[PDB]
Image (cartoon, rainbow, N blue to C red; front, top):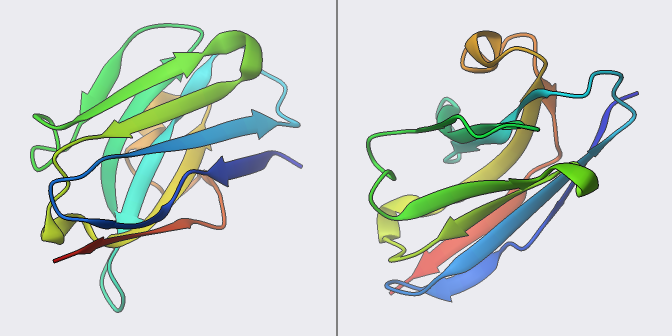
Length: 123
């Protein structure tokens, strides 16, 4: 009954920026891990970035650490992904995903999953 509401995707030129947002509801714990994985068609999903809602601990994949910033608004149970300096390689469906525990979050297996947001980076 946890629901993840995703927004902010689109189709943008390389070098440009986007901001994704994800809001969680229906959960029963005050702090938890939330962020994004991404998937290219026909390939396995991979972690992008997370933060603990209600806190300040972040993690980024190597491929995005210089360019993407994740933040949280605890009162809105919302996280944001500021995506700057977009690369052609960044094209994927971006899935908001949640787990109560960040070490579990990274595994994906037990997470709650959003429907996903297409991000297309164009030349």
